[PDB]
Amino acid sequence: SMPRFVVQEHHARRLHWDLRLEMDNVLKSWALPKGVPEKRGVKRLAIETEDHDLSYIDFEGRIPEGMYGAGEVKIWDSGEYELLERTENKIKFLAKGRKMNGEYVLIKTKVGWLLMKA
Ligand SMILES: [Co+2]
Image (tube, rainbow, N blue to C red):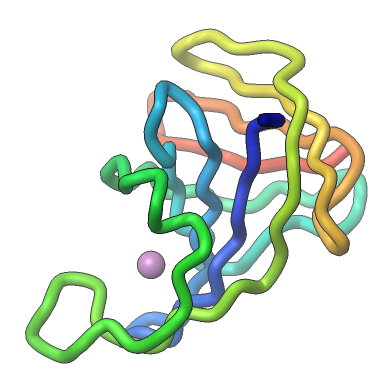
């Protein structure tokens, strides 16, 4: 297998959380400066970032200074997910994490992305 996701908490120069979905045979990724929305109605900024390799999904440890992405990476949540809808401008999924669960939607507009919870 079932596709998985991870939310990594990344203590870099700007603290943020990275949401990564196993999708298109890579980790499709978004940085969340204020984290995953944990209740209905809350609309969080999501910043599309570069694809990562599948093997990175379980990573924890320190990205060294001088490298792009420096800082400590921890797993904040993880689990399987079920894809419900997908186009170039919308991704709707059921998350099966311990913190991130139920349905969520990523949307793309002319200003970037947003992440919301059902
Ligand atoms: Co990051």
